[PDB]
Image: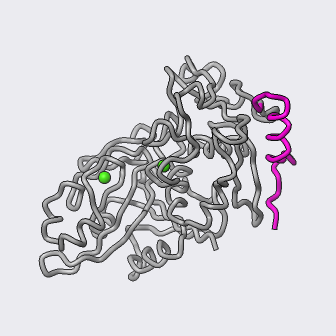
Amino acid sequence: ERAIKYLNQDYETLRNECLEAGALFQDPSFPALPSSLGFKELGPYSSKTRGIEWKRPTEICADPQFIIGGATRTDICQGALGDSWLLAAIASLTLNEEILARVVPLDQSFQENYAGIFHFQFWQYGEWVEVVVDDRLPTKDGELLFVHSAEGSEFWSALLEKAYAKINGCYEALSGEGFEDFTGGIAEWYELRKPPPNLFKIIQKALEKGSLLGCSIDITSAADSEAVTYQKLVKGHAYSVTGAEEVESSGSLQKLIRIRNPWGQVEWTGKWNDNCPSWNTVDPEVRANLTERQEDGEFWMSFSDFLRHYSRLEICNLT
Ligand SMILES: [Ca+2]
Ligand SMILES: [Ca+2]
C-alpha cells in the first residue's frame, strides 16, 4: 500500500534534489506568503498578521528537534488560530500508537538528511494522502504563532498543523465544529443533555480501541466565543477526551473522565481538578497513575459534572 501523493509531490525525491543542490526546500505550492496565512481574519490586510515573519526552526532556536520525549498530546498547544477541533483531534490521535506512526513518519529530522522538507499522511476520503511542507513557520517576536509544543525546541506538531493548513489551502481554513473535516472514518455525535444510558462505557470502549474523542460547550452568541466559565472551562472551544476511569472514592464508585484543553493551559477548577482534596479519598497507587499537579491543559472531572457542563461529544471511529 502506498499513500496518494498530494499534488504528486514526492518527499524522497524533493528532499534529495535539495540536498544535492545544497539548498533548502521552498514549497512552490504553499509559499511563505500572506496567501498561505489566510483571507480575512488572517488576510493580507488584517492587523492580526502584523509582524508575522516566516522562519525555519533553525532560526527559531539553537537546536531544533522534530520529536522530543515522544510525540504526545502535551506537544499540542494552540496558537493564535481558532483551530481547536483540529488540535483536539491531533492530541487525541497521539493516544493511538499505530495511526500516529503513519501520520507522523520518523524518517525525518533536523540532523540527518535535513533539507527543510518534512512530510505527513492524512486519512482522507477513504484513502491515505501524503503531504510535504517546507519548514518555514509563521512566527511573531521570535516564536511560533500557531501550534507549538510545551517543549520550545520540538517541531513535529507545528509542521503537522502546517501540512493540514496546506491541504486545506491556508491556516485560516483550519478555523471556524468537529473532527470530520480533519479525520477519516465515521463520526458519531452525542448530546450530553440526552446521553445514551451506557455512554460512559461507550467512551471507555472508544478510547481503548483508539478512536478520537472531542467535546465542547455551546455558545449563546459570538461574543460568548472562548468565554471562560466560573469553573474555568472555555466555551465554544474543543477539548480532547483522553481518559475515563471508574474509581473507588471513600467507599463509593465514581466515574471520572479525563479532558485536555488544546491550549495546554487553563483547566477545570471543580471537583477532581489536579489539586482537589478529593484525590485523597482514592487509593494512593491509583492516584499516582491518574493525576499530577501540572498545568498541561489536562484534568479530570466526574462524569456527572462533565454531563452537566459540556454540551456535545464527538467520537470518530478511525476503523
Ligand atoms: Ca514531545
Ligand atoms: Ca493538569
Q: Quadrant of the C terminus?
A: bottom right
Vertical relation: 242 (above or below) 131: below
From the top left corner, tell me how far across and down residue 223 is, in percent: 41, 37
What's the colour scheme? Answer: one colour
Q: Nearer the viewer, residue 302 or 293?
A: 293
Vertical relation: 256 (above or below) 234: below
Q: Is residue 158 left or right of residue 282?
A: right
Q: Is residue 182 left or right of residue 144?
A: right
Q: Residue furthest front?
A: 112
Query: Residue, x 70% and y 38% (percent of image)?
Result: 114
Query: Residue, x 37% and y 71% (percent of image)?
Result: 244
Q: How many marks?
A: 0
Q: Which range is magenta? A: 1-25
Q: Quadrant of the N terminus?
A: bottom right
Q: Tell me which corner region of the image, top left, top right, bottom left or bottom right, holds residue 55.
A: top right
Query: Residue, x 24% and y 47% (percent of image)?
Result: 230
Taking the magenta stretch, the answer to whether it contains residue 5 is yes
Q: Is residue 57 left or right of residue 134?
A: left
From the top left corner, tell me how far across and down residue 72 is, in percent: 48, 55
Query: Residue, x 77% and y 64% (percent of image)?
Result: 127
From the top left corner, tell me how far across and down residue 132 is, in percent: 75, 44
From the top left corner, tell me how far across and down residue 234 is, in percent: 36, 47
Vertical relation: 179 (above or below) 255: above
Q: Nearer the viewer, residue 279 or 64?
A: 64
Q: Tell me which corner region of the image, top left, top right, bottom left or bottom right, holds residue 307.
A: bottom left
